Length: 122
Image 1 (cartoon, rainbow, N blue to C red):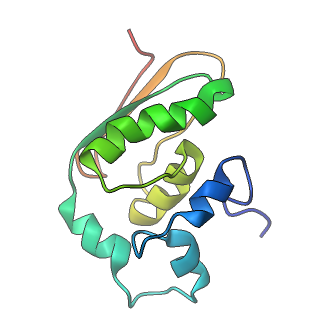
Image 2 (image 1 turned 120 degrees about the horizontal axis):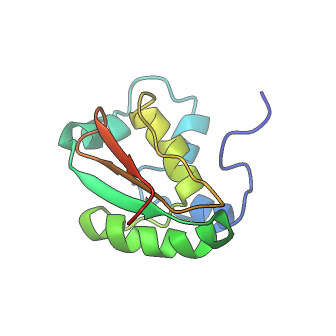
């Protein structure tokens, strides 16, 4: 195609560096992934609830650190970006994924992956 979401955006570097036998959707995907490992799958079962707010993309970089504090808090030590989360998630949830806006305040949340919640923060 062209891009794969994390095709060298920003912190993507630190992301690609992150893959402690965890999600590593990048390595796995590129690893002729198809349907064997069952990584994101095994973690998919969890279907744990999560919630994070999105801010001006101009702060996406910083928001990433703030996001982790929200996710990594209830998630596994991961240094992914909001841009990668959408892609990484899309894999574990190609249905309802999270987006990012750079102009106004936004909010995204989920309980498993099916039903999600959105808002403009208040």
